[PDB]
Amino acid sequence: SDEEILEKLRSIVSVGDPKKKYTRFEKIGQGASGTVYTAMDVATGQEVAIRQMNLQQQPKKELIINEILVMRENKNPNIVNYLDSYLVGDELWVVMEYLAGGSLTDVVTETCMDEGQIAAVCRECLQALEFLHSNQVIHRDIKSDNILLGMDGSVKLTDFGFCAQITPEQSKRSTMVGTPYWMAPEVVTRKAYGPKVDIWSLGIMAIEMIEGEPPYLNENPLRALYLIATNGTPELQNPEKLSAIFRDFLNRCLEMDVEKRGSAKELLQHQFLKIAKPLSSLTPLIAAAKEATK
Figure: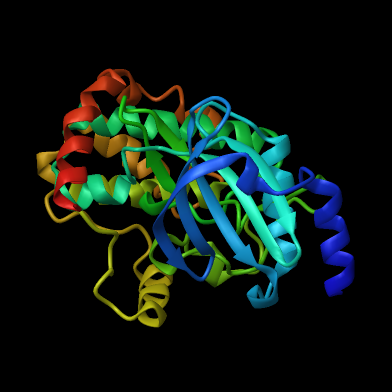
C-alpha cells in the first residue's frame, strides 16, 4: 500500500529538507532508477551522489525500501557507501558517496587492462562478495556497470535494487532479476540458485575485462539466455593469450556444476589474485576512460 510505504520510508529517512544540507547540484544521469546528481555536502565539503526519486512513478517501492535497509546494515570497504536518505512529500532522496573515476564499464570499453590490473579488480569484487554472502545477501546483478571506481583506483560495488536476503530455511531463490548476459545458466535451467550466481557473473565481468564485452552482447537478450543455458561455459576468443593461472581462475568462476564452482571465500585464496598490481595501477586507465567518455 502507498500509505504503508511512505510511513515505513518516513521511519528510515533523516528528518527535514536535504536542500539545506547539500549544494552545487549537477545532473550526471537520469533513467528508470530516477535522476542522479553530484552535490557538495555543505558541512564537510564531501562530494556526494544523490539519487532522486518521485515515488508516484516507482512501480516496485518494496525494492527501494529493501535497497536502503540492506545498504544500511551491510557496510563494507568494497561497497559504495550509503550516507543518508530524505523524504519530502513524494520525493525520496538517497545520498551516496561519489566515485569520480566512473564505472568499470568505461574502463573495459575504452582501455585494455593487463592481468595484474584484472587480478586487482577481481580481488576487490570478491572481497565485497565474500562479505555479502557471509551475511546472507546475494547481489544478483554483478556486472561492470555496478562496479564504481575511485580516482585512486578504489573498486566498489553498488546497486542493491536486485539483491536477495536468504536464510537456512530458504537458502535458494528462483526470481530472474539479473541482467541477462551476466546470468548464471542455473537461473534459467532450474528454479533454485544460490550465492554462486554472483561468482558466475564475476567470471563474465572478467571476460569483459579481457574482451571488452560479455559473451552474446550483440544478441537479443531473449536469445542470449537460451545461448547461456545451452552453451554453458562461454568460450574465450583467444584463450592462448592468457596465463595458465588466469585461465584456471576463470574456469573456477564459470564452472557449470554449482558445487564445483568456486565460492567467494575459496576464490580469495586463488593464486591468480596474487599477481595483482597495486590498485594505483588502475589510475591511468580510469583517467583515460574518463577523458574518452567526456
